[PDB]
Image 1 (cartoon, rainbow, N blue to C red):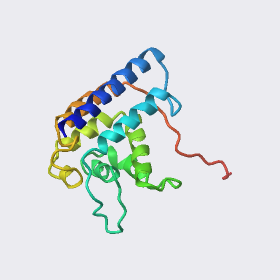
Image 2 (tube, rainbow, N blue to C red):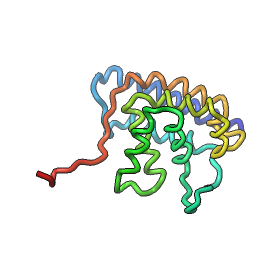
Image 3 (cartoon, rainbow, N blue to C red):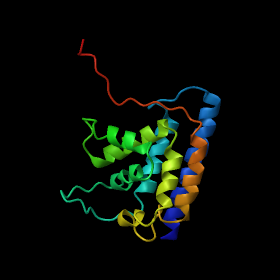
Image 4 (cartoon, one colour):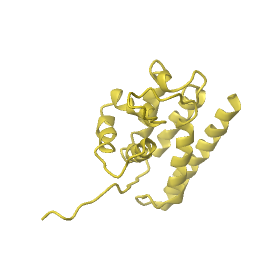
Length: 167
């Protein structure tokens, strides 16, 4: 068990570290077309998927790692803005689809590293979604969360929607 967690950690390190080193020289606002960037998320998702439980949702909708993020707002003000955007965003059905988009917003706000730290420091509630020996409940959680700082300097900008029918 302890092995599976370490795998993701080191895997996340390269993601961040590399992504930063790749963004440094690049010197320009990144977008949803940068392979290294998209690579980061995938890794992140697997980290947030390690240790999940069953869906307690009344409507029986397994939110996966979405739920664990729905708590972020109830910990940091700046989160209640993006955690709402995804919702008021049509075309985005699947819960995981919301979480993936959420991260992108937390990435733009450069508050990602912050939020994550908030969760780990609240294993009192973060235990509802994750097991007792989950990644987000272990050292790796804090470690990676403390490393996501180097990403604050990154200037991303993803596309969510756009209208032009109204005059």
